[PDB]
Length: 101
Length: 101
Image (cartoon, rainbow over all chains, first blue to last red; front, top):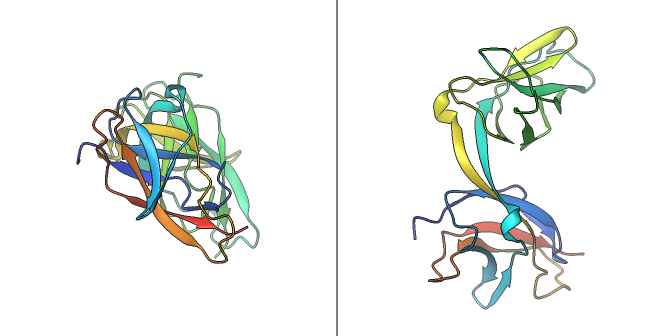
């Protein structure tokens, strides 16, 4: 089906032990009629999650802005947050650290 | 504001050069009245993106299932896809590779 589409899995590697919590982004699905399946030609495994683990989210794709100082010899972790244009009200900050060249 | 909340940034590091495309997950926002802001006490930068870069998405949080063989000496990349319970129709596969212990 084309209706079901996974956009991505936050991580692409993990221990063969499993039990590792991850998240995947995808298109519309029904939390009551959906499941995740790991598999190979002769093996199949299922992701462990409930309906409460299926969240409606907004995703913003953007290119980072160059940092003020391009000659930094050490990492600089700055703030990143959403900000409304109209009233300029920001969200809580989330860290992102710029790396030297 | 508590209305605006970022759940996460796919990456937490990048070159100070900027221009690096990333994506961030967050709660409800208005694509016409929203913006991303990078900053420090005395500096501010803006994420580069348009309305077409704000997507409504579903995110599923789940724990990976242990792989069949826990004694693998080399990485095994298997398939991962959504599958409907009712009609068992799967989505295209996305790779995920199990790592040895």
